[PDB]
Image (cartoon, coloured by chain):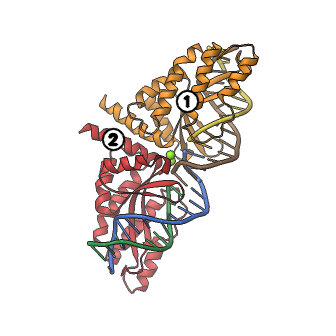
Chain colours: A red, B orange, C brown, D blue, E green, F yellow
Amino acid sequence: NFHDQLKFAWLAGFVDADGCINAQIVSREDYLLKYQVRVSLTVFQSTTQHFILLDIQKILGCGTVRKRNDGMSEFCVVGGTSLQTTLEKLLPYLQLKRAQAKLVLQIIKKLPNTKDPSVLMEAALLADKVGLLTDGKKRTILAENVRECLKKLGHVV
Amino acid sequence: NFHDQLKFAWLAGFVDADGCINAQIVSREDYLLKYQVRVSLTVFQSTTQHFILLDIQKILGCGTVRKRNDGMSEFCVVGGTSLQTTLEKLLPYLQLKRAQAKLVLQIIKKLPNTKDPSVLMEAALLADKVGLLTDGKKRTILAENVRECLKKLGHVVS
DNA sequence: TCAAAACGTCGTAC
DNA sequence: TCAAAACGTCGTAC
DNA sequence: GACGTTTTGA
DNA sequence: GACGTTTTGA
Ligand SMILES: [Mg+2]
Ligand SMILES: [Mg+2]
């Protein structure tokens, strides 16, 4: 199978250098619990070399390619079912981001049960940990927010 | 064997994303012909995770790591005899930057003979071609500079 | 005279 | 009600 | 890179 | 990233 391991290792190298394994709390008004924990693997490259994200998509067999209005393209794999399959491909080779993976994999464990406020609360605390491994300072929605809101919908978390 | 090839594939993966396979013309005033063509593979990372550049050095067996003053670290392999050896490791796996690799290997071919003013000239012209690919155009110093100043040192190039 | 080691920093690809 | 597909953009790690 | 935002559609 | 520059030293 090792042709495939060469490609996964290569991709792991690329992700480690230029990717994004993430978990975010996004506001969703039509959700009962008001919040979703979005999980994603993302890879950036300038649109000039758009073709490589298409190659990554082929290697993985999952995920969407888009162009950005600023001259960048993104390859993206959202959602637990598809993203678990992918992370377990890259997990033996990831180095710099093995930690954001495992956490995200622990999050995906709970996504099926996330209608339950305590389970949602758990995924939200986990997202924050992933938030502390990303350079990003943009993180505005936290677990503190999900809990106050959950509190206020009259749920016991 | 197959383990080393997995590390070289990962590293190829890394260089394609945050590497720099380059060829610069640097002015060296103590040089007879005033110019040197520098070949280099460089990998960048935040000093936050300075450790990854030491992992890359160990895997390769060559290169220097430094801390920059602004919070980044670079791992760098300079020069023909050691940078050649690194390229042939990565070459089968470099996707994005294999052109820069192949050009730089054509340049390393002639560095031993770069005391010949026409040989330095074929080398400088290959430096600019690498440049049309490493697309951050902060370079002022081109082959036309070398050729013309070579002309004024009394040397016959074209 | 060569040329790597080590360096400082501005622009944009993330 | 869920949640991915698709999106726009500033800050900083390259 | 890492966010938040708007759209599609199950 | 991808330059140009100073330093060490063979
Ligand atoms: Mg990076
Ligand atoms: Mg890159």
Q: Residues within 10 Å of mark 2 (few under 14, many from 20)?
A: many
The type of residue carrying mark 1 is Ser
Q: Is residue B10 above or below residue B119?
A: below
- The answer to whether the residue labelled 1 contacts the one labelled 2, judged by CB atoms less than 8 Å apart, is no
- Distance from the alpha carbon under mark 1 to that under mark 2: 25 Å
Q: Position of residue A76 (x, y in %)?
A: 39, 57
Q: Is residue A70 above or below residue A113?
A: above
Task: State left or right for residue B30 relative to residue A38.
Answer: right
Task: State left or right for residue A35 relative to residue B38.
Answer: left
Residue B7 falls in image quadrant? top left
Whether residue B99 is visible here, answered yes or no, is yes
Q: Secondary structure at mark 1?
A: strand
Residue in the picture at 32% in, 49% down: A58
The response on whether ligand 2 sits within 8 Å of label 2 is no
The subunit letter for the residue under badge 2 reads A
Viewer-side residue, A111 vs A15? A15
Q: Is residue B79 above or below residue A109?
A: above
Specify the label residue A124 is tagged with: none
Task: State left or right for residue A44 relative to residue D3.
Answer: right
The type of residue carrying mark 2 is Lys
Specify the label residue A7 is tagged with: 2
Q: Which residue is mark 1?
A: B40
Q: Quadrant of the C terminus of chain A?
A: bottom left
Residue in the picture at 42% in, 35% down: B94
Residue in the picture at 47% in, 38% down: B15
